[PDB]
Image 1: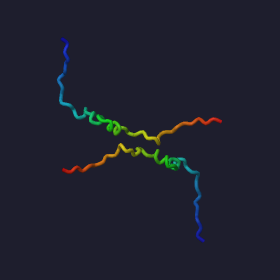
Image 2: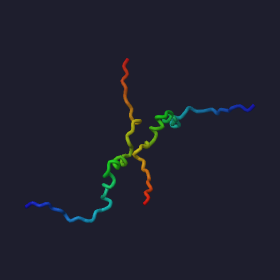
Image 3: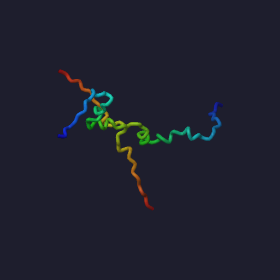
Image 4: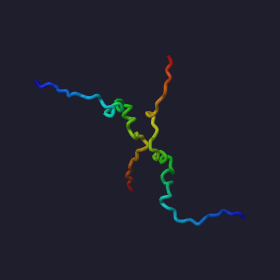
Length: 49
Length: 49
């Protein structure tokens, strides 16, 4: 019978763990290099004669 | 009579001109590498027993 195989593992390496930095909604905002604000928006206008 | 002296000048060098980038309120905001938002604030709390 085909059974689920699990390879022998080694203790987790600290350098592998990145998950601690984006497991929460607020965190995903903190991870942004720049946050989108209304004053960054430039609206184009097509003025006719 | 002491009069205001003005030294002979050379044409303005383009590389000298930085003023075009912050002569307006909005521009001073655009010049910011990061804008301050409410979600960047962390308020400390002193919980007593």
